[PDB]
Structure formats: structure tokens, C-alpha cells
Length: 162
Image (cartoon, rainbow, N blue to C red):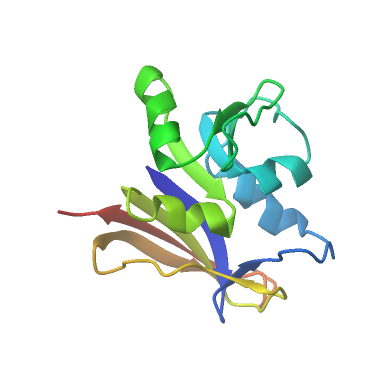
């Protein structure tokens, strides 16, 4: 299972309840990362999400409710309910998108990690969860210095070890 998200110098991710705005470049990666397959998302996330469900992207809703539903999307309550779907759907891949509440949920199950270290700084009140970098291994990491000094980023790909 993979985890795709972007972190800045400070290591921020997003907001919890501000609704400021989203970047076009930083947004393309957030989705393009696992789009086109079984991408998980928090209930709160699936809501704000540009669309429900996503066009060409299988989404999943994680909530403590045992009756929670979604139009087209899949409804799960934890990392056990998601793996259950992906279990019956060995054709598609399982990659968690968010949110933070969902990140630390699969942190102990994630077999692969994806982080984008952006040189520039980003605002927000929500920080990234405590990842066990010691439990995982870095398989790839290279920074990309674009024209914009703040639009820079590093693509890190980690693989959970035993």
C-alpha cells in the first residue's frame, strides 16, 4: 500500500477547516499520484473532494459509522475494511490519499511511501503524522529545482521492509 502526499520545509500537508485555496501545480500531483485506481480518502475528504466520485478514480470513504454510504464510492471504516476491498479487487492497486486522520491509520500497513519535499513554505494548521521511517526504506529520492524557487520539490519513494 502506498501513501502519497506533499510536505514543505516545515513538513506541513494541509488545513483542517480554513478553506483558503489550493495550488494548481501542487494539486495535480496530489491526485495524479494514485488516480486511476483504488484510492482511499477520509469521509471529510471525500466530501470537499472536487467531485464524488472522482472521474476515472475509484474513491473510498473512511468513517467510524457502520452505515455510512457514498454514491459510487466505497465505504470503509478502517485499514481493515479497505484491505478487504482491495482483497476482492486484486486487479487494481491500493493507495491512500488522505486525510491526516487516514494517514496514521494505514501508517502501520503502508508498504510504500511517497513524499514531495517542497522547497517553498506552505500555510496550514495540520501537520504530517509520525511516520516510521526506520521501518521503511528509501528506494528513490531526487529534488527537482524548477524555475520558481518555491515551486521546487523532491520525489521520495520508500518501501516498507521487514
